[PDB]
Each structure stands twice: as C-alpha cells, then as structure tokens.
Amino acid sequence: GPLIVPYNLPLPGGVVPRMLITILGTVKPNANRIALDFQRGNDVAFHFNPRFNENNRRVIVCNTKLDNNWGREERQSVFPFESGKPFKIQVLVEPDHFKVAVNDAHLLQYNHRVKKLNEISKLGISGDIDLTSASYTMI
Ligand SMILES: CC(=O)N[C@H]1[C@H](O[C@H]2[C@@H](O)[C@@H](CO)O[C@@H](O[C@H]3[C@H](O)[C@@H](O)[C@@H](O)O[C@@H]3CO)[C@@H]2O)O[C@H](CO)[C@@H](O[C@@H]2O[C@H](CO)[C@H](O)[C@H](O)[C@H]2O)[C@@H]1O
Ligand SMILES: [Cl-]
Ligand SMILES: [Cl-]
Ligand SMILES: [Cl-]
Ligand SMILES: [Cl-]
C-alpha cells in the first residue's frame, strides 16, 4: 500500500556493486522537488534532487554533503519527471558510480565521492511524491 514520506530505507551493511534499488511512486500535482539521499551517518554520499522550478526551469541537482557542507553540484537538464505522473527510479550501484535510470531510460551517473561504500547504510526518500514501493535486490 502507500508508504509514508519521508521514508527511510535501511541498506544493511551498506551498498555494494550490483545492488539495484527500485523506487516506484507518483509525482504530486504542482510538485517542487524530489530527493533521494544515500546517507553515511550524517553525511550524504549521494543526493539526487529533481527540482521542478528552479528559476522557472526543471533541473536535476546531484551533490554530496560532508561534515554538514555541500560540495560542488552536478546538474543534469534532462528531466524525465512530470507533475502528476507515475515514475520508476532505478539506482544501480557500480564499482565507480551510481547509475540512475528513470522509466527504464538511462539518466545519469554519479562518481563515488564517499568511498566507504559499506558505510552507506540508509536511503532517505522525500519530497512531493506519493511513494508506492522502495526495495532492493542484487543483479
Ligand atoms: C532549503 C532546502 O531545500 N534544504 C534541503 C536540502 O537542500 C539543499 C540541497 O538540495 C543542495 C544540493 O547541492 O542544494 C542546496 O541549495 C543550494 C543551491 O542549489 C545552490 O544553487 C546555491 O544556491 O546554494 C544552495 C545551498 O547550498 C539545497 O538547500 O536538501 C536536503 C537533503 O535532501 C534536505 O534535507 C531533508 O529534507 C527532508 C524533507 O522531509 C527530510 O527532512 C530529510 O531528513 C532532510 O535531510 C533539506 O531540507
Ligand atoms: Cl548511515
Ligand atoms: Cl512538471
Ligand atoms: Cl563503474
Ligand atoms: Cl569515504
């Protein structure tokens, strides 16, 4: 059934290459933001943040937060989300990157800045979505 947002998905023993995380939900009408935050304690190893209205443009911001400071943003203008519509986000952990696909299309890759993959042990999901499912498997 419905999951409550913000939602915290534990990743027992951290992430590993070949782990595939799948998030299903629906963007609310008039959404502003979505965020997936892969955490290593207080640090955010990988923040994946679609913004629906940043100076009247849609953009995806990726970043990492270390010791309560945000780093250098990486931005992607390809924006596969739409207000009101169902989505699937898949994050595949690879040896050197997270790889993100939305609705079965490749979107972006994010190079690992936090290198202790085994300590990335929680995924926070938040923002203007109805969350249907969040799960992981090994491929
Ligand atoms: C104000 C806000 O949105 N705070 C949330 C925080 O947002 C920051 C994050 O998106 C970073 C990524 O680089 O950018 C920051 O904005 C930048 C901006 O992009 C730059 O152009 C320039 O202007 O500098 C600013 C400041 O660096 C955003 O402020 O993102 C975190 C993580 O998702 C949010 O935290 C969570 O909110 C959830 C809501 O339910 C939940 O509480 C969760 O537990 C929180 O960790 C901040 O709220
Ligand atoms: Cl953690
Ligand atoms: Cl939209
Ligand atoms: Cl890789
Ligand atoms: Cl590290």
Image (spheres, grey):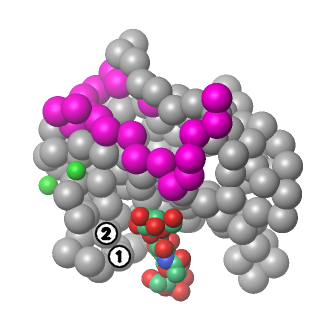
Asked if the residue under mark 2 is in contact with the one under mark 1, i.e. CB atoms within 8 Å, the reply is yes
In the visual, does 132 lie left or right of 82?
left
Report the magenta residues as a range: 1-21
Looking at numbered disc 2 in the image, what kind of residue is underneath it? Answer: Lys
Locate the C terminus and report the quarter of the image it occupies. Answer: top left
Is the shortest distance between ligand 1 and the CB of mark 1 under 8 Å?
A: yes
User: Disc 2 designates what residue?
Assistant: 65
Q: Secondary structure beneath disc 1? A: strand
User: Disc 1 designates what residue?
Assistant: 70
Is the shortest distance between ligand 1 and the CB of mark 2 under 8 Å?
A: yes
Q: Which residue lies most toward the bottom here?
A: 55
Q: Position of residue 95 (x, y in %)?
A: 27, 32
Q: Name which residue lies at 75% across and 82% down.
A: 55
Is residue 89 part of the magenta span, yes or no? Answer: no
Q: Report how far apart the C-alphas of labels 1 and 2 lie in the structure.
A: 4 Å
Q: Position of residue 131 (x, y in %)?
A: 63, 41
Badge 2 density bin: few <14, some 14–19, many ≥20, Cα 10 Å: many
| N-term-proximal mark, 1 vs 2 | 2
Q: Name which residue lies at 48% across and 61% down.
A: 62
Q: Main secondary structure of the magenta part?
A: loop
Looking at the image, is 46 positioned above or below residue 138?
Answer: below
In the visual, does 40 lie left or right of 111?
left
Q: Position of residue 19 (x, y in %)?
A: 35, 24
Q: Secondary structure beneath disc 2? A: strand
